[PDB]
Structure formats: structure tokens, C-alpha cells
Length: 91
Image 1 (cartoon, rainbow, N blue to C red):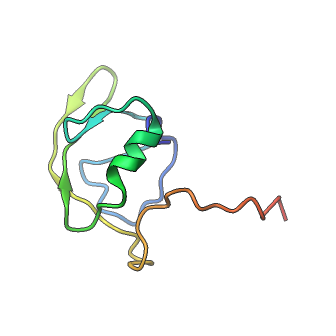
Image 2: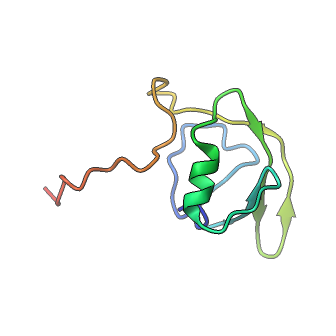
């Protein structure tokens, strides 16, 4: 998820910033050994703040400045931060 995207909720500008299988080289020039570090580094710092995120596309790199955002339907919280309880077995 952190070092390997696959699916992310929209409802955001998504302009110049996309995540659907793409790979993130680094954020803010800061490298990461494991997804844990990437999540820890952010520690929830979206909405108003700005960061530089490089993406890889078929051996191509792009640089765009965008302003982070927060769930427009939940400003009280930001980022999933993994909270999906294992309670929902299936039903």
C-alpha cells in the first residue's frame, strides 16, 4: 500500500497525484526502507501542508506541486492509517 499502491478512494483533486499500482520512489527527498517508515514519517500531515512525491510510469518520472487533502466527508480524521477492524468476517 505505502510502497505499492493498488486502489485509493477518490473524492480528491487527484490532479498530478494518482495511486493505482504505481510505485513511489520517495517523499520530500526522504527515502524509506519499508511502508512502516513512510506511514510513520507522514504521522498525519495532510490538508494545507505541501510535499514533493515522485511517481514512476513506464520508466517515466514527473514532478508536480499539489496541496494535500483530507476525507471531504470526515475532516475530524485524516488518512485511513489502517483501522479496518477484523470484526467484519464476511457478513
